[PDB]
Length: 475
Length: 19
Image (cartoon, rainbow over all chains, first blue to last red; front, side, top):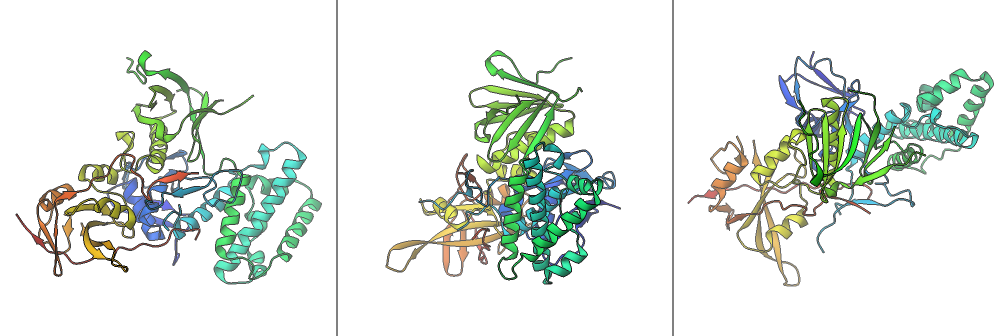
């Protein structure tokens, strides 16, 4: 009965942690935008999210065509895919992360709803062994992991107490610490001694007694939980991709992915927001390939991927399937968008449809006010179109007006007009097929707002590598 | 502080003169 997309959080208001889609065909992007909006996620945060196929263990590229009834049996989760370790800035041993600030706040990576979704997703991955007890060897590491997992289960229940507005003791009786710890630790407890069970129960009941009502807020419990999860789980917020073949090649010595007239994994390629692209064979050490800003393009031919660096060196990869190659290319392309270029994509095979449209129609992403001002200020008659920073389906046509700030010093006043979709500008009797068509008609015309007039002389276009709040700066 | 503040555009009613 339709495509059921699973949620880790239903957003404010709540309800069923899923969204069912009945439309004959939809893109993965349309799905994510619809869900992001329902959950309260804002437009500057939309591109952090993607759809994960939990059974096939692949993510969908944003141009993936979902079809109903054909895909009614797919098990998909809506999740944060693009992650920056230490974004909260709680580990001093690693750099900070922020959105570009105004020229010469809006610098925070996440909005309130993206943070709460991240926390709910983190709890799911934690319980699902993103950090396994089995991966440990020494008594010191095992003891630390168990004690930390109990502290995490304590934070999990404290949050629930605050969220539902009930004391910690009534939460502790409805929810067990065993349901808030990694599954590998839960299995360990069950298989081990009855006296060890009694002891862990008493250690946890003690953790509950050292709780102070009014000491911490819901937000502080969440940040600490997430920051502890990062410390416990080095794999959390990262992706390790298995490949069947891996080669490094210099371009002026051969063509990669060449058409010629699958096997067990030989390597893993690691991709992280703060560390770029690394690899290792399956004594172990991650070799470094490049950062996202070093990539010129990515070539995808069947299940074969080629990552091209500016110096013409290539990382050639054979993935287990076409769906695995599309998952992988959309991971590299998604981090490239966030760290290097808001208005470019590395491979047409996985390009976000809303971005392809934006590039051809000369539309900017959800830019904050100081970035649009820096674009309109050079000349009179300048204008631009950008996606709204609050509304997912609204475009903003913007002009700058002569104004006088307090002191008598000449200032700049912005006038914002909405374009809605068959794109229509609110106040103009015409209707257009594309925004490029609506913008081409706009060229040379005169805009009237109250008693003021504005010459629509030139449309500012997105420039390659230009900094804005859409760019994520790695400290 | 930790999180992205809301930013809604104040939008206005248009009128276009052609040629």
